[PDB]
Amino acid sequence: RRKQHSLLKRLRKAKKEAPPMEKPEVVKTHLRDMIILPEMVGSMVGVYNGKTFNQVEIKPEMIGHYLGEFSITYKPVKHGRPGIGATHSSRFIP
Amino acid sequence: KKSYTTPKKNKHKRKKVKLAVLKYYKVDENGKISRLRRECPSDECGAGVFMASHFDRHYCGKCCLTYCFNK
Amino acid sequence: MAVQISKKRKFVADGIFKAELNEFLTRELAEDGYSGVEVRVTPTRTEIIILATRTQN
Amino acid sequence: QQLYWSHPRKFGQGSRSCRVCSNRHGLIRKYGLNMCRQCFRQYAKDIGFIKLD
Amino acid sequence: KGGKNRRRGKNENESEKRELVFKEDGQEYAQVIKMLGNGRLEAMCFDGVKRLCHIRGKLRKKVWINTSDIILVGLRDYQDNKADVILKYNADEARSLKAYGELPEHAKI
Amino acid sequence: MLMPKKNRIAIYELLFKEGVMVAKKDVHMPKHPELADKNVPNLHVMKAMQSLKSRGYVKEQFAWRHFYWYLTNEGIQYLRDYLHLPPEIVPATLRRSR
RNA sequence: AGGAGUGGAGCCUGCGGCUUAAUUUGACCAACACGGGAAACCUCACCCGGCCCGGACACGGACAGGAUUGACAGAUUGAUAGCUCUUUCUCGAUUCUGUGGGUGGUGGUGCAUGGCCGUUCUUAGUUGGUGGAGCGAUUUGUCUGGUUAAUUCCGAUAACGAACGAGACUCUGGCAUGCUAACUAGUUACGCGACCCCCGAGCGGUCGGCGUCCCCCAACUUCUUAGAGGGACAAGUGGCGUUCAGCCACCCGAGAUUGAGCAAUAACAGGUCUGUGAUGCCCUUAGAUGUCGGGGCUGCACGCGCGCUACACUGACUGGCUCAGCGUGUGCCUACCCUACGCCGGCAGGCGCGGGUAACCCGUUGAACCCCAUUCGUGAUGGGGAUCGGGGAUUGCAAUUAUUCCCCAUGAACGAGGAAUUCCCAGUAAGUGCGGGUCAUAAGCUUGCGUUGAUUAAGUCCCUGCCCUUUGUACACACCGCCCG
């Protein structure tokens, strides 16, 4: 416990106060590191990427893993149309 | 490297309100001095300073991490 | 006051003292006709012979 | 003011610093260097070395 | 070019990218119609009026303006038929301007 | 503050006694060992000498990440009156060098 | 003439293009495993959030019922940043506020510069004085010839006498039973006593053999170590040359070349403002280009470069035998070294003790290829180990886009490689391991070192390129030139 204190109290707290048969709002984090645990389950957590808080519901099937595996931090990728110098042919103009 | 882009908030440091000073000692008759709330009990405190009358919270401002009664 | 560093490291630390001084002085005695130094440790005493042309200034 | 200004630097390339001005990038330790390779050259004449090979 | 030499005695370069005047008063966007020689060139303005465009100092042999493509042209204060080139853009820059909806949506690249 | 009023004295008095100060360029010094003993947790030496230097009264060298401040006659007069000292005292040095 | 490869295949890494909120940036023979640049954080210049001033000094303003400082809790917040707000104590001339003025910047400009480095250029080139020759730009000296690795010498001579580079020099290798001297280096000799086997003559003792302890007030310095010296000079002989300068063969023997360091004139719009508290000018400077948290430099339908591992029988696999060298190591930077020995575990590893400032301890460095004996059998095979699932350890504040290491399982391309192309002449190429560098954890990289050790040449100007002379030129931004319809 190196001031993971801040997270684990908010989760239990928000889970308690929330109506029955309804999930809480969110607790947010810039921390992408913390083991998913049984007690954490049922909460909803937003996880900072570089700008964006991608929200996720915690399953009992996610236990053992980290938070940061369920939020990506890049666009998967598309292409493309090779550019100009994209080879030993691009050159000349005047 | 390039110049700062516009915010829509920024505010620096609060002005730490311009309260009237020393009414903490009450005079109704002399030589009597009618003290209000208790003066701070720590060894490192001088006990010449007042404690906050901050009810539902009771806190020495000379202290800055310790000695917070609340009842 | 001990112990004492390795013989290899003994020469390096002497070189660092010889060099740092020689650029410290050059930034103050430039107008006085600086020309170098010559250090000598002697029995229970340091000598730092501050060579310059005009000892007056 | 603030309650922080620092965070653990205890190992790595940021907890040692080289003697140019507190320059880096140019990772250096050798035989008790703490001395920057660009200036090491300028101290070839100065004492520590004279070039012979 | 294809490498060669003597092309480094002089100031490499490049367009570290960048941005973006307009139009201004008598200073607007045109498209290259033809590609004469000697130096001058043709370019129909985007409004509807034709004109004949002229190259400008520096941009001389420092920037090639192939045929077909948007380009920034000042109009001469008094002359109608002849007009004066400025400030070209990039093909990417021209399609961003088109997507914004500031130049007329008529020409393809 | 800028710094306490205690820690001013402890620099200005120490300078008067040796006739010279020296320090290192850091901002993570924890208590500043190597005199001023364990009551300067920050810049304070460098920050106070610079203001003093602006108004003359001292000269400053710098070489291989170390300052060197040399007190001068004008600052001796200032510091003497500023710290309410005898009209003729210099404990820094006063003898002929042979 | 040949040797081994690259280009082909899988993988690592750098570069381009594409993508992206950011995928920071320099560099295009003389860039591209290069910027010590193997980036978890830091680094960090980039992107997104939050905080701080570390805005000197001057002048004016504020101002001792006072300029000002900090903070609990609650709310807010990634946050336990009094950051903000609620709440109300605390600090006391250090300040705050306005103007003037500074300061910081991995901000820009290497086409404003210093310094350094690379390259032209590893070739033999380069210059002034006085005299001579020309109206002058210039030229002679600096050469027809012989000779050398070399503007190296001989010789010629309107030039004469000189300087820089070449050489000389420094380091390293190769030759010492000569010299100098050694328990932080050895050898020999016994004194030995102890262990061991008769193993050989003899009996087991002794004599001889095997190492270790014992070794000294023993003897010595061959081996090891490092100092002073000597030795190689074309010296001698035979050919050849003007018989000059030199060249070839041979004796002695270490043959006149073992390998490196240092290196001229003049130049380049070569690289570096991101090594520099080197530096001009410009920009920015509180809503900061100066600090904490998170992400990225690793993102892929593609193109190229440097390398690593392979395609088996001259092999793989499992046992057995037996040899080395250059170094390095805690007491350093801020928290950290190299390891013997004992114990526990299949392994990674854990744990208990001890030594090492180092010819003293690790380490008589008990390394690999190689060597000796089993097993496999021409089969994409047990060759190859890519891809991929599960589990165990170590470093750290943190290991996810798997830091590294280990165990079991999974078992791909690849069966000798087009057009092209690189590098190399003797302990050299090639095979093979090790130390140092970066390093909290980690080399497929780079820099050095040992070990095993060939084939082919003793040449030439064909290609590519360079030096000197002569010649031609519409060229001098110098043929990557100029110029015509």
Image (spheres, grey):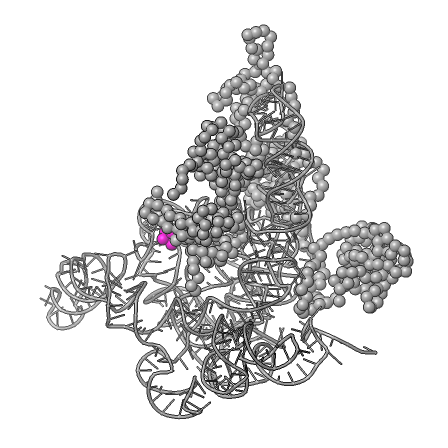
Q: Position of residue B20 (x, y in %)?
A: 64, 19
Picture layout, residue G83 above or below residue G393: above
Q: At 51% from the left edge and 35% from the top edge, which residue is drawn? A: F75
Q: Position of residue G199 (x, y in %)?
A: 18, 69
Q: Which quarter of the picture shows residue G225?
A: bottom left
Q: At 64% from the left edge and 48% from the top edge, which residue is drawn? A: A73
- Tell me, yes or no, whether the highlighted magenta stretch contains residue C9: yes
Position of C13 with respect to G150 (left or right) is: left
**Which one is in front, F52 or B64?**
F52
**Which one is in front, E37 or E68?**
E37
Q: Is residue C9 visible?
A: no
Magenta span: predominant SS is helix
**Which one is in front, G230 or A57?**
G230
Which residue range is magenta in the image?
A: C6-10
- Tell me, yes or no, whether the highlighted magenta stretch contains residue F11: no
Q: Position of residue F92 (x, y in %)?
A: 44, 36
